[PDB]
Image (cartoon, coloured by chain):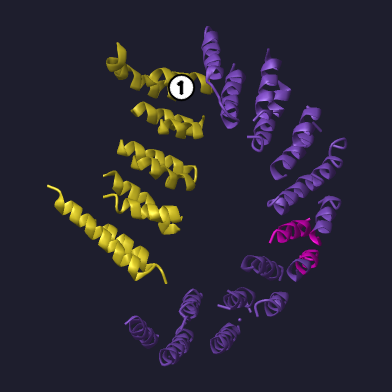
Amino acid sequence: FPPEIQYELWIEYLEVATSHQLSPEHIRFLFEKALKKTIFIAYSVFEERISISKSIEILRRLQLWRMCISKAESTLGPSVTRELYQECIQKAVEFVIKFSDFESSIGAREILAYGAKLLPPSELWDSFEIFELKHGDKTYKDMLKMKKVLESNMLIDSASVS
Amino acid sequence: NSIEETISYKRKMEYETILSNNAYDYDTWWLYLDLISESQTFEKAIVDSRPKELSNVQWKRYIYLWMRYICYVENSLLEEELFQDDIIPHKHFTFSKIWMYKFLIRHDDVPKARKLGKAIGLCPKAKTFKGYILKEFDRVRKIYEKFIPSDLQIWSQYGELGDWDRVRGIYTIALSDFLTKEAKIVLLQKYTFETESQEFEKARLRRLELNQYSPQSWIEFAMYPTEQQLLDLAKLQSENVDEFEITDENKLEARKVFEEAVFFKEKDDKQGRLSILEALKDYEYGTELDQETVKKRFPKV
């Protein structure tokens, strides 16, 4: 039936055959045959608890999909997740901001400058964010006023838009 | 029955997957070995040995050897070449010819993962495995290496095999908020006369050390009488030398309410509790909070 009806077969066939078996290579191959969206998720769910990095490579191989990968990478530990966002950038800015928030926020200089690059990437809550980052220091009114100036310039480029 | 080529097509495609690098080829070694396991058995093991050795080189020592004992059943010279450090040779000479094929593989595993930061933890697990198989030969090796947090674990284990524990705990505490918590809990658990003696030569007084001396008096002098008078002396000596006494009035109010029950005793407890509240409320704390708030607002602007 080819890639149309075959999917209608294949979703139940996967859910069932995975439910049955004891051996990685056979089912691995079966997903391989299979692959030609949810399939990635079943498959990834398999790899994490039988086959891990390989799975992460598979997820690496849309916003929701980006959100997942990041979750599984966090499951492998924190460090990757900040890394994941950089992949993520290329509404998404809200997510990159969501990752960057605890990134530099827990921190790193490349990450903070990235926070600036993202905040400037495209917003009053973000202004509260940068203001929070400035307030956190016991880092200067000058850079802060320059920041509000740049965001104002963004207000200018935004207002200039038709 | 007739799924033989199912394995042969999958295993050929698994090896057929190109692998540039060390970890990529070692990742493929995990795939085809599992395919070989489920389904020239010696030459596949030999080509697997060269792939793991020809890789990460740091992580292949734990990857290759972990599937060597299973590969051997389906060995002594190959393990010594891969594991190749001074303490590992000392561990081998004590339990190679004396005890095994389980022991001789476990020692090479200990020298692969360590050679470390987890040396006091691994050495404590080595003595627990060697002694079990209340031994005085392995415990003395730990006691000899103690003189040259982690030592309290080996001290509490050797004593269990509180008469001999005082000999080890005195040496441990002689040489960290967690380190003193282990020595304080050991001298308190051993016991009510010696529990108070250990409290006097440790608790001294701190917010944890002062709170520990109060908890020691609750358990040690619980079934005796003079818990209120001794607790009032500790809070007075601590407050004078060292606003943050909300846990002393709260733990004392819960200790009085938790006591099993009269009228004259309960009314006397209300008089004693209210006397501390009246004396506490008239000692500079709602007034102290607003004072620092005005200074904090003034300091900024």
Compare residues A21 and A152 and report the one nearer the observer. A152
The N terminus of chain B: image quadrant: top right
Front-lying residue, B159 or B65: B65
Residue B149 forms part of the magenta stretch: yes
Residue B275 placement: quadrant: bottom left
In this rendering, position of residue A156 left or right of residue B194: left
Q: Any magenta on residue B286?
A: no
Chain B tint in image: purple
Task: Considering the whole magenta stretch, tell me its main secondary structure.
Answer: helix
- Mark 1: give few (<14), some (14-19) or many (20+) Cα within 10 Å: few
* Percent x, y of residue A81: 43, 45
Q: Can residue B84 be seen?
A: yes
Residue B283 shown left or right of residue B46 in the figure: left
Span colored in magenta: B146-170
Residue at left offset 75%, top offset 60%: B155
Let me know if residue A52 appears in the view: no
At 69% from the left edge and 80% from the top edge, which residue is drawn? B200
Residue lying at the far top of the rendered structure = B2
A90 in relation to B189, above or below: above
